[PDB]
Length: 279
Ligand SMILES: COc1ccc(OC)c2[nH]c(=O)c(CCNC(=O)c3ccccc3I)cc12
Image 1 (cartoon, rainbow, N blue to C red):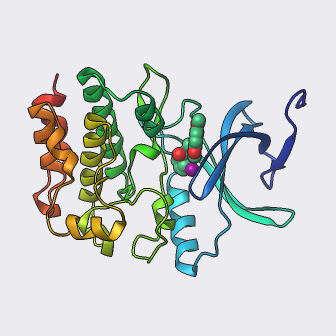
Image 2: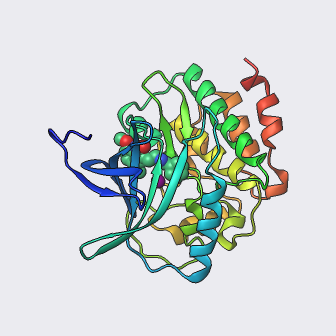
C-alpha cells in the first residue's frame, strides 16, 4: 500500500496504474508538472498537467495519434513517454501526460546558473541531442520534434547526459496562430511560421540551441517582439549573438545549421560525421 507520510495521492489514471502526488516538480508555460508513481513498477514518474485550453478537432486527433507512437520508444537521449489522457478535478480540466521524470530540470535552467560552458561539455551534449534527433527521425513514420529548445532539453545530472523532452507537444503549439506579446519573444525556423517543414526544422532548432549554449544568451534579444524577429528570420538576418561565438568550429556548425533555406542545411548525418563530433 502507499504510505502517505508527507505527500497525499491526489489523482489517478482510469485504471489507477498512475498516481499523482501533491508535490509540484516544476512549472512552465501551459503546464504544471507533479511527482507521480507508476504503481505497476514502483517507479516515480512525471505527472504533467497541460493548461485547460479548448483544442480544435484536428488538434485533439493529431495529438492522440502522435502520443500513441511515442509509447514504446526507448533511447538514452530521449525522455520516455508512458501515457496521456484527459483529466478533471473540481472545476479544472486538463490533459495529463505521464513520462519519465527528470528531476534536474532543463538545459535553460542550467544555462541560467552557469553562463560559461566548457567546449568538452558543449561537444558531448550537442552530440547527444543529435543522436536523439537521429533516433526520432528514423522511426516509422519519422518523428520530427518541431519545437526543440533549451527549455525542453533535460539534464540527467550535473555531469550526466541530456534527453530531449516535449515529444509530440508541438502538435498543440499554435505556430501559425496570432499570439499575445508576453515574455521573451521567440523565433522559429523560417518555413515553420507557415508549417511547411521537414526533418530540417530540427536541424535549425539544434543550431539555435548550440548558439545559445556557446554564447549563453537567447538569440535575438535585440528585438522587442516576435514580429521584429520574424522579419529578420525570414530575410536571412542572423541574431546579433551569432557574431559572439568565440570558437571558429562551433560557429561553422551553427552557420551550417541555421541557414534560411531548409534545403541548404546540414543533415543530421553530416553533423554526426563532422570532425567536431568525431572527437
Ligand atoms: C515541464 O517542466 C518541468 C520543470 C522542471 C522539471 O524538473 C525540475 C521537470 N522535470 C520533468 O521530468 C518534466 C517532464 C519531462 N517529460 C517530458 O518532457 C516529455 C517527454 C516525452 C513526452 C512528453 C513530455 I511535458 C518537466 C519538468
